[PDB]
Amino acid sequence: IPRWRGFNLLEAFSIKSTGNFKEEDFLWMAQWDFNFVRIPMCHLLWSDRGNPFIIREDFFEKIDRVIFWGEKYGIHICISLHRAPGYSVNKEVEEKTNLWKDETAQEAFIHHWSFIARRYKGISSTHLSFNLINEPPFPDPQIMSVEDHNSLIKRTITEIRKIDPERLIIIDGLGYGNIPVDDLTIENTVQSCRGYIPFSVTHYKAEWVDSKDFPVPEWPNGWHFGEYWNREKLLEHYLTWIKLRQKGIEVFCGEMGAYNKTPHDVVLKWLEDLLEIFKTLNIGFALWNFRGPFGILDSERKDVEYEEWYGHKLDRKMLELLRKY
Image 1 (cartoon, one colour):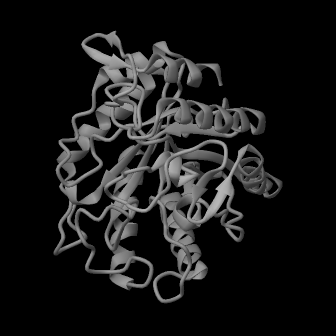
Image 2 (tube, rainbow, N blue to C red; image 1 turned 90 degrees about the vertical axis):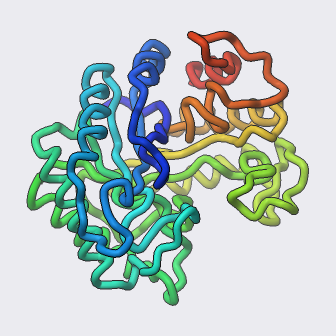
């Protein structure tokens, strides 16, 4: 199958999301030759904080439409749990339980994946894959050991595959999607890495991370938690990732990009280096937004001369960069 190139769509991402995805997103990205979307979902949109086994199945009509649009536009759909019982990197709501340790949270997690597996059974893996959980933390036995992660992921896959043996599963790396998971030699899986290194470029002035002391963005030699990064250091990083292929595991970058307070020249210089490594290493990518601050449209950068695109504002230079690679 061809390398995945595309975007994340965020209409089911937050407790305040409506689940109303835009068919125009699919039409536009198809016309620009992209072939992939990831859909990070918040389980509280169809569940309950008190009872994690609740599923309001009508919500999934919204996701059905997305999967329908994928087939129609030639866009692979990867549906993801951005929040699940006991886990989210999103701080908008605090999980009272810890998925990585809590037996009940884990049963609820599998219960949700089982419902989804049953709903979409018989949609081929060419059209639809499952990304079980977004961005698990760094291992720390106090929260999540490597073995807590691996046992849960294996159990979950086992259940999904009892329902749908051929279902392709995407597994995020540890350390928020940055560390390859070495003991998950499971057939028909992809591990998902990240394209946010270095944070002084991609997350400069980001409100939801502790960014106050980040240095001014620069590339090369951008700063990431005390270390300086260049093209060479990126290359070595992703070269480590693709060793997973020696184990028969594919690799893909499920989120990438830079926020909208970094100067446009720094973003494009960094992005091109990254994209060039990806193309060279045959690593698929997904930009964190299509429309939005990390995206090519309506990104609200104060230093971009936007192009009019059907009433939206298009960053043509960033778009053309993506289409080149």
